[PDB]
Structure formats: structure tokens, C-alpha cells
Length: 92
Image 1 (cartoon, one colour):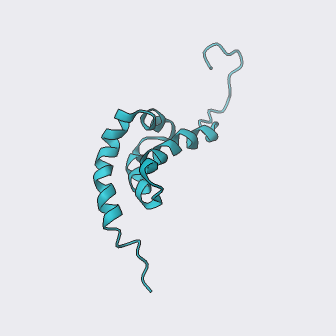
Image 2 (cartoon, one colour; image 1 turned 90 degrees about the horizontal axis):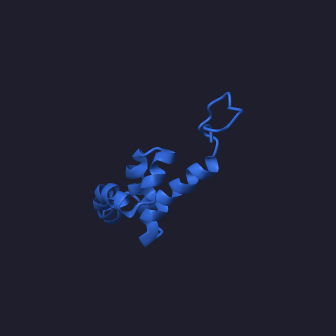
């Protein structure tokens, strides 16, 4: 890394490894939908756990314990939102 590297970058672009950012980040979403492919379900909790930055979320989305806590509060909403989803019911 930038520790033992002779030539250092001029511009500090943190948005370099975008493929990695969405990579582990996607883990946040799939971790929720791990019980179902409910885009409205995991999308609900994902927004809650979306408080952790792209990379800062990686360490969380990879730890079961770290998820349970964060996904905990969001979980309770999981049922309510997935059950009382009277908003996703488009009328004619």
C-alpha cells in the first residue's frame, strides 16, 4: 500500500475500487434477502443498515453478530413492512 510505495498518487480518489464497494455492499442486501427474494423486504432493512458507508459497511455485512444487532431494529420493521405492505398494492 502507501506504506512502502515509492511513488504516491497525487489525487486522493477513494472511489477507485467501485467494483469492491458495491461488492461487499451488496452483501448487506443479500444477507437480508437470505430468507427470500423480497426486493421490498431486504430493501427496507438495507436502508436501515445503509447508515454504514460503502467500505465501512463491509466489516458489518460480513459478521453475523454485527448484522443481528443492526438488522435487529430493521428486522422488527421487516415483518410490519412486509405484512402491512398495503402501499405496494397498486389499485385500478
